Amino acid sequence: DIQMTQSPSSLSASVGDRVTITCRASQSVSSAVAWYQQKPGKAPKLLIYSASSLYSGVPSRFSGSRSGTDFTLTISSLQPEDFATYYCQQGYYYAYSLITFGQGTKVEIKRTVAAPSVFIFPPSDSQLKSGTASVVCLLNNFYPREAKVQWKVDNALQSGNSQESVTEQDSKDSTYSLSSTLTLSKADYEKHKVYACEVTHQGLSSPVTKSFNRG
Amino acid sequence: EVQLVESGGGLVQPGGSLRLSCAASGFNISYYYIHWVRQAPGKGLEWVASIYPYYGYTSYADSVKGRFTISADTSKNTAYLQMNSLRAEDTAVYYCARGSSWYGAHAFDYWGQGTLVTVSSASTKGPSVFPLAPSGGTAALGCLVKDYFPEPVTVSWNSGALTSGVHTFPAVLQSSGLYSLSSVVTVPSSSLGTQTYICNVNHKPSNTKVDKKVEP
Amino acid sequence: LSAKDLALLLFTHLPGNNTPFHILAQVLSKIAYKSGKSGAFLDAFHQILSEGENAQAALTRLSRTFDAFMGVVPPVIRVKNFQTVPRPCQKSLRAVPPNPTIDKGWVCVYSSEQGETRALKI
Ligand SMILES: [Cl-]
Image 1 (spheres, protein in one colour):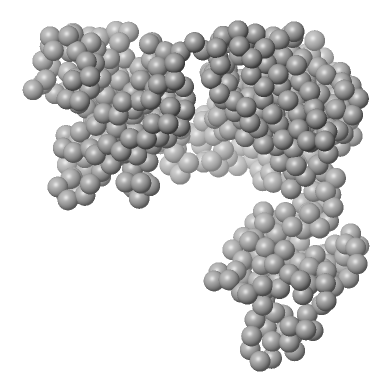
Image 2 (image 1 turned 90 degrees about the horizontal axis):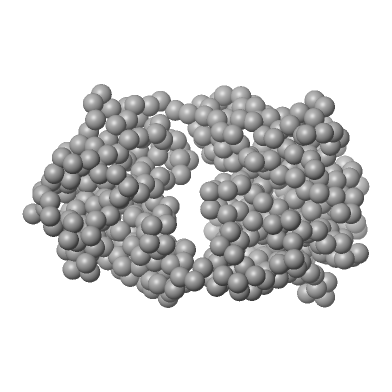
């Protein structure tokens, strides 16, 4: 069976940079390869058909080429809206031909490091009345994506009781926002005083801690 | 113009059946391949099935062979995916797509919008909405939309009037198997006395609409 | 590649005469040329034909999606009166809306001697 191996699996590139995504066929597939752009949770868009032909509605900065079994998608000058997963796909129109997708290449927009602004939120009285406690830490408008958010409860490091969510890269300025949510039973919440979110990030001279005292 | 409109998605028991519809306009489905392609949480595109309705050529991924049947009604210009013996691993956004050619290659030029199939024994449940109370110059506040199933929920602020500084986070599946997410906004501190902030939450799957006033 | 040369190429793909698509072909060719995008417009037109769509559909889609025509006010065509508007276009004459643009399907504004206006809608 045909394999289409894409490389790299992910890449960061700045606005105006030339981007090169590679797709290797396990054996000869002639020029029978297409390229797609997919925004998260959205319908893929056809960019290139027959290895090198630009589909309608596709800006000129997108181009495709073939050297033997090696297929290349080229973005000549990356734009801030170009973050997406790009897929190659092989297929002939002959009846019962196999369709083979690549595993995708996630393209991230690189920009100047930006430190997060950090906020902490205690659980609401309404949630505590309902019998649970969620503590929320917000990291706003930062780059890069990578951040360490540690929870401390009366200075005791927490593990396995938090979950993170991150926004899609801003379509203008390429920053991220992140939420870390600490989940405690009401009983475990009421047993401690000091709730702290400690953030380590490239843009921070020294970790930033935001804290409150239960009461 | 050419379009593919999908329907039939939603929440189904493990072992259950669900039928997706791909309604075509602007072309005759008889002379194209119609494909189903799905995307599971944290996975890439997986090709599922195809039909060439003129000749009735059907093709299936090994992962769905025996359980899924693809079909077409040319009179309705519609293709169907009959999904039987559904499993957790079939949970995904399902896309249909048109397979076209110029000189013998096979490209997917038109795509449906995608429909979410959730395979689970979990009950539909609406969220509780909790305020994230504001704590120089700029204050952060928000709403925690907790313990809903299935996806999705929508969040607006002040019925869509407030959009500057709004960040609505992707849903996270909690260990419990219920979703949560937060929506936050940064506003002038000076406005906290005077300006009202209300998050408008809609969980269509459970018919749950909540407006939560967020006060300091 | 001049506006007139482009219009004549497009005409070879259009049935009949005095049709809305003929008015559209002439309006788009003139704007495409003036914006220095005649070659890019023709390439885009040929790509849409290659998809099995007819020239009427290709010109309709390009009017809505090609960047040269985005937010461009339709041109004025001077007429004696709305009776001397080519017969096959008379069906498509409408009242001129507040902010008419090519990309919303407003092809041109017919301006009568008596100072009245109608817009050609596709
Ligand atoms: Cl082809």
